[PDB]
Image (cartoon, rainbow over all chains, first blue to last red; front, side, top):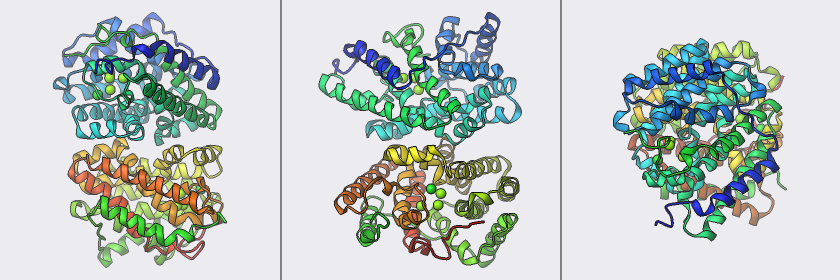
Length: 296
Length: 295
Ligand SMILES: [Cl-]
Ligand SMILES: [Cl-]
Ligand SMILES: [Mg+2]
Ligand SMILES: [Mg+2]
Ligand SMILES: [Mg+2]
Ligand SMILES: [Mg+2]
Ligand SMILES: [Mg+2]
Ligand SMILES: [Mg+2]
């Protein structure tokens, strides 16, 4: 129970083992994108404008905590479109607010038009439609699976059922479909649109996020977390589960290395950069705080 | 030795059927097209593949189209124009799947896919259907001799079925079939591809078993039974049971979806099995309705 309410006893060791895995299997360190003050302010003002119809104010410190995943987990050496980068910054942030909101305040009529306005600001006409549909599908999925029997079944049955749910629910399909304009790389664009890009990266993103967001999520009655599949109060069982998940991440990373050079660079910067950001995000460091609290 | 699953044909067919009777129960049913409807479908198919220069016989079309007739969910059909579109799109992209890639002319074929979608679908639905068709034929082409395909199909079942979510065409299927039903929940699962991911393994394991002999003889590697030594009876049976286990788990989780959506999901998997066991394409290594379409 309370023994199952936290992965704190494993925090240091799992962090060390995560990093050791990346040093061995990815090697290349992720890179932080440095926005100018003008760029950061533009992103944040677009974020505020988009969530203002929903009546909640979001502090700069909160936005900065949301945006760090984009700053850390894109692929700076391959960036060609900084407008598409800023779009991903904004879209990520405003839908992370949605992910944190009480569903009672999920106003599709007010929010969906703001998502379209973002896409139309930053993307060409064709890209705007691809990014928008993926944003729409992400916020719709997050809404419709709150207290759903489907989510309960897919999250409590097996790791295979759980990660299949997370391809969409964690947002990585959305991410790939709004991020391919950053790179203008033909192969990457196709893997993004088939969702093979998302499926290749789902476990490495999800396992890392689930470990560090476990304590917050169980305190909030949130069940979408693979470590609820094991008794985290049982050290031996946890260790076995955790090794199985490292094995999952490793197999994925090695198969990702079969993709073309630019595509695998982007895929691996995403997985490894998310890890680096996750270990520095105060959202993931106490059960409830001013940057991870539920938005009432 | 590993060239054939023929020794297991009878047992595996019986066990598939037993599994379905225990876990699905509800039988699929065949859509009966009128003569005019079937002729409209076949005319559109021929018109679409005509620019590619290879004639396709009525018998071959009827072979391709059976999967749509058997694997939709007739109780819930509301839009027979969308149904006919799925018939045409399935068949013409099946021809593409059988073609030598030297014959893959995107500039001639892609506008034929758009013309089909624009005939049968509303404007939003036509874009969704067309994008999925484009994605399907581009994937089939770009993976024909790709190291990515080798890596995903030789590493583990997990990597293989991940590749099949697109390659077998099921994501395509869901995104062009939701208009048949106009069921709001089904439409969203189609668009997230959750629908496709729930049904991939039950469709792929069946198709792989019955297309193994043909595929191995053409040097096609996209088949999960190449992950086991099919010449080792003990190893095969262990592998085959693990695949039955996968289908069973998927089906039991599908039953958590809403009633109509799960009817559609399970009719797809079980109807595909019914059609596969009566399609002559899946009965010899090469015959006149499964031969490679070479240049
Ligand atoms: Cl949750
Ligand atoms: Cl193949
Ligand atoms: Mg979430
Ligand atoms: Mg969350
Ligand atoms: Mg989380
Ligand atoms: Mg194929
Ligand atoms: Mg084939
Ligand atoms: Mg096959």
